[PDB]
Length: 163
Image 1 (cartoon, rainbow, N blue to C red):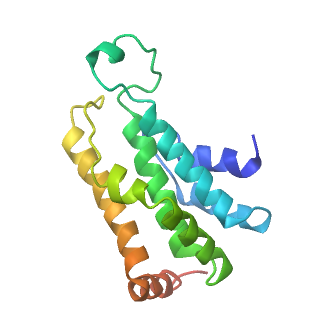
Image 2: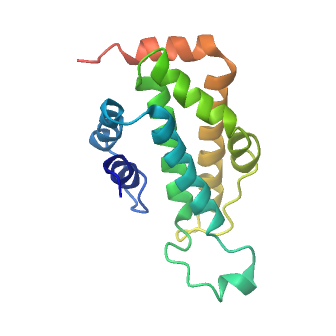
């Protein structure tokens, strides 16, 4: 119910389209009122909660109600897009360190859950490409955490057309 949470939810909704540049900018502007640690943590919690809501097998698939069935992969991918966007766009020092500390605290999400991610079913038959997309985004985030110099340069490149 907090404003930053509504913004993150908009950016990471189950809709087929988005996030737009404006959605991401809106999430980012919460840094003037909310710590980056919390923005990062809520993004991870949404990611985890939407991974957990999926059925394990056909028995539970048929018996749990499961709104968003076959489109949960989108929330997962968009949450990773938000994390990548924050890493590239927040200020050096306090803001960036807060994101990184939150990700490191929960590093298993990247090193296990995302690394091993499977999309069993998606509504358009394209499970393979969605799975690949998610693992790739997870890989990029891990690279940013593993190689500070790469992250530093990408952040500098990201400013080239800032205005």
